[PDB]
Amino acid sequence: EPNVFLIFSHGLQGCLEAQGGQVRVTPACNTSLPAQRWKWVSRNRLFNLGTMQCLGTGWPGTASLGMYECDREALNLRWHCRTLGDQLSLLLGAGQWRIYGSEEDLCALPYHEVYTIQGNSHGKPCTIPFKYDNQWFHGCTSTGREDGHLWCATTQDYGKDERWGFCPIKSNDCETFWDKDQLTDSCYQFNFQSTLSWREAWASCEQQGADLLSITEIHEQTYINGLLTGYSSTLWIGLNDLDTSGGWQWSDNSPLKYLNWESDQPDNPSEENCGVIRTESSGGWQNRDCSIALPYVCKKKPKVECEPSWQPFQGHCYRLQAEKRSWQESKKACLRGGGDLVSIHSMAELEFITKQIKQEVEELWIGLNDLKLQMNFEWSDGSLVSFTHWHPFEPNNFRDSLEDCVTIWGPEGRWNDSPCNQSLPSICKKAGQLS
Ligand code: NA
Ligand code: NA
Image 1 (cartoon, helix red, strand yellow):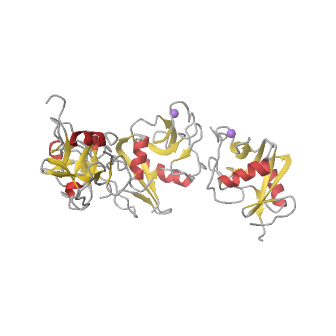
Image 2 (cartoon, rainbow, N blue to C red):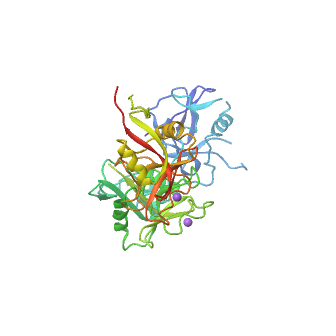
């Protein structure tokens, strides 16, 4: 019971209590008494755990506080955490209202929508509270189920509407609700029957201890397209440019090292900011309006010294090769120097390279490339690709050439991809000696 809280008045010096059908302030604050335990629930109602009822007052026309069945409409059961204090002070003839035991205001523990998994409600969130077999529930329950799985109604009256779904769980395994890749031990959840917005889908994955699908490897694309063959669907993935336009990122902060945009994508930069995978294109990526309602896919996984003319940063040595060469020839020159084309794994390393090594050189080669397999970028030095810093609407050279290599471009230190044909200076990286 982490969302539950007591309501204290400094002006009356006591906690708000609900007895029978009445509401009072008692100086005897006791966090154990459910009569004093409150909880925000759906549709801006304030729920009491002792009475299993909702705080209410009269509509304009008859003013007092009382407890009422939460589905009563003949009374106003709606409150706002910002004005609740003023309403309580008004109706009790009081000062300042806070959560008991803290300096936090009554807006500190807000109601969060919990989106359902599978069931028959297309991902619609739990209606809190809901009635089932004439009993109120202010949370998920397994009563009425043998397997013990937690569920909830998506209307307030299950007996009437029979709309429901499974509740999301934060698990250390991937048992009931997930397809697991045995090779990578990564778990995937295709909610074909749900219809949620991107942000809603994001929240759903998050409250399962997961994130929207990121596709980081060529294999991962193949495994994903695999499970999708036969189905006909368009599903949200973690891809978006909400922060920076054209700056596509995975919601789970994975590097944008693999790409599978459809031929004409992405487009409509002014309206479409979120990524979808499609079965029609055999797993191609599109960008769409983030507010549209779609099925979605979740994912979870249960001080050195340098040689002369080189400069140190962290544990490596860096050097500018000012002579303009091709990407491959730039690399060959780095190797003869006992190093390789620079690999960049953090923002601090990037800043060092850009401010200290590149300086006013306009554009130059780094180690990132997709010569081996196209649309799948890797560092020439074989290092793990953990970090990308693409310019807006980059990369995009796989859209023409069959071989793409990467440069640092301009003062921000962001990256382009380009034909390796191009003649540019470059930066080299090798390990340093400690010291
Ligand atoms: Na589009
Ligand atoms: Na490019």
